[PDB]
Image (cartoon, rainbow, N blue to C red; front, side):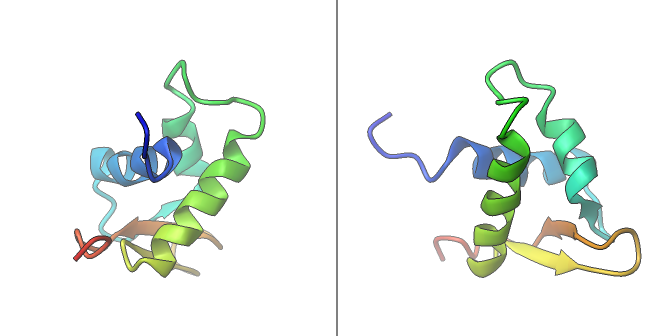
Length: 83
């Protein structure tokens, strides 16, 4: 691995894919699914998800959801990340 876009961001994409979440999944819900891997940092990993998600919303890979389920809810858009 000489070039990865953050294994935490790749984990977020696939985490929301595991749940589906048509309405959007809270950062707390995504965190609970993301901490189930042994390589995941249980300490500062919540900040790593917070920043990975936010960067993916900036790349139009995730859609920022607010109000319906939680304050910071998030879901998949498309493979628009690289396209």
